[PDB]
Every structure is written in C-alpha cells, then in structure tokens.
Picture 1 (spheres, one colour):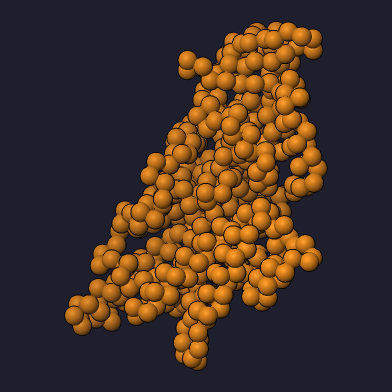
Picture 2: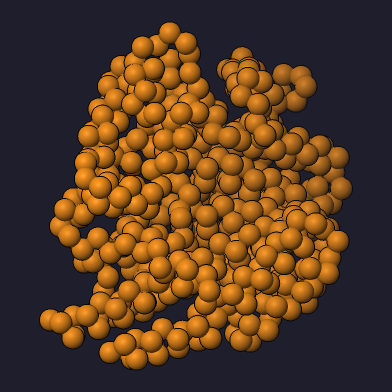
Length: 206
Length: 234
C-alpha cells in the first residue's frame, strides 16, 4: 500500500509536466502573434523570449529542481520495478525539456482561415456527440440512436472532402482532434450478428 | 478487471428489495449521519456513527462487529460499481449522496479504515460517472482568435475555466479536503508511520490522481499540489 501510492504520485507528476509543455506552447504562439501583428498590422527578440523560459515560476519545486531529482534518485534506488521505471523515465525527461518542447511545437496548426474554423467547430460537435453515444453503447447495441449515429458518420464521410492539399490539411486536422480513437472504439463496440443497421454504421466507420 | 456477467448478477440479486435487510442503511438527519440495521433476529437498531466509533474505541464488541460489517459492505458496494456498471451506481447514488459521504469521510473521529472505505466508494461511484472524460494535456490544434496578445498563468486557466460547463463544481469541497489532508500529512515529521493511516493516504492519493486526470484541477493548483506531493515523497 505504501509503494502503490508512491507510483500513483509519480503518475500525477508525469501528467502535471505535460500541462507545463502546453503552457510553453501557448506562450510561444502568443509571442509569435504579438510579433506578427506588430510588424505586419524581430527574430532575435522572439528567440531570446523563447530561450528565457527553458531554465522561473513554472519550476516544479521551490528549490530550483534539486528536490525533484532528489526524490527521483531515491525512488530509483528502491526495489519496486514499476516505481524505478517511472523514476528513470522522469529523470530522462527532466533533462530533455528543450528537445521535447521544440519537437512538439513543430507539430502545431494555427487554423487561421475561416473555413478551417467551420471545420473545427463541426468536427468537434460531431466528435462529442459520437463519443457520448459510444460511451452508452450497451444501451442501444441491441432506433433514434442508430439513425443519429449513421447520419453523423455519413456527414463525416462527406466532410472528408476532395483535393490533395485540402485532403492532407483535413487529415492532419482530424488526427489533431484524435477522431481515430472514437473510430477504433466504435469498431470494438459489442455486436450481435444479424443487425443490418449495425453493419451499415460499421461499414461507414471502415 | 470487472467481470460484467457475475457483476450484473450480484447487482440484480443483492440490491433486490427482498434482500434489503442484510444491507445496513445510512441516512442523514437533522445534520448527522445515522446507521440503521437489523440483528440476526427481528429487531431494528438505530444509532449514530460517532457513538459507534466511541464505543468501539472503548472496547464494546457489538459496536466493533457492526462497524466491521459496515466497512466490508461499503467495500462490496465499491467493488460492485467498478467499470461503470450503471444499473448499480444509480441505486447506490440514490441511497448514498455526495454530501453524506463527504461528511462521513471528512470527520476525523471515525476510524481510518472506515474513512478509506468511504473514499474508495466516492472515487468508484460519483467521480467515475460520465459527465466527464480523460483530458489530453497538450492540444496541437489552436485557433488564431483564441491566442491572446499576452498570456500569463491566470489567463491560461481562465480559458479552461470558461470551457468547463459546471458553474458550481460538485467535487470542489472534495478537492479542498484532499488539499488539507495532504498538507497535514506532509507537515507530519514522518509521512508514512502509522499503518492504518497509510490506507487512507493511498485512497486519497488515488482519488486525487483520478480527479487530476479528468481535468478538474487548475495549473496553479496543480503546481501547489505537486510541491506537496514532492514533500510527502521526501
């Protein structure tokens, strides 16, 4: 019981480190937007700003990071295998903040065009509705829900669109929304053979 | 891992009204929590948890046996509701409310074991419903309008607060209690000394972890809790 709580605490710390990356990404985008709007209603200044954050309110501990490494080392010295694995992973990630931050920043989409805004809104709404229905799959696996799901899937299929550049942009956008997780979850929905509507929606998902 | 078949059978059998006698009933009355149960024969006992714990500390056998039965029943309820078997959590939620469990868990006079059982039920009943879902920390897609001219920490959580649809969070007091408990345990010279308290500490830690993974907490609160967690670890 004393070791499982330590592992859970490590998981909490691991998750809480990602929101820090999100905040750093947001700050970088904000600095970009300020520079772009100011210049066109510079590179050195934004570079200095980006370099400043990496190494101090965002610090994990008030000791400047010494405490975080201290607990990581102590946990690594323990006998529990999962705990040591988590501690080692955190230790390695602690000294590679800049690499991970830049790698994640490179994969960023701005969605400036108005059309992109409409696709974002509609896709988000459909994804939320489909996820809500999937979470309650057991209720309607064996009606209004069937037609609603079929309509949502058909709307998404039409939404896919045409055009090589448009195709690539939309595929990247869908990956950003993580729609493939909803698709895979729907595929693994419990099924009873002989339901025509279920086969139809499965074909649409495929 | 939950087994849907046997879980469903036990859900339909133990909660069946004919077998309601075996299940102890807790009710909040003007407030204090009162336990009502029935002996092996046809007599009904109505008392309160505080006096039960006091007598159990004194050494009364009947109080200890009744308390043990209650905690084990609570553990059975928590295990039953694992993996979102809604047929059960509907009945459990109607019987046991968020405020009632908060009152039972927060108060210190009760034994540590009972508090841990209440925490487990709270996590596996009310927190694990589906007005929620796992929140991805880093979102690659960002809108050109959303990006503010100047961004600070408070501005960052402001948008998250606006996104949240719950005007009055139902678990906010739970987060407050978790913060106070962790502050007290870290304040203690030996964070892990009492064997019984370890169960409750693990339970609250698990509840906090699941709460964080659902996006309830804010970045500033996340950092503060991170400092406290680092303190308790070492």
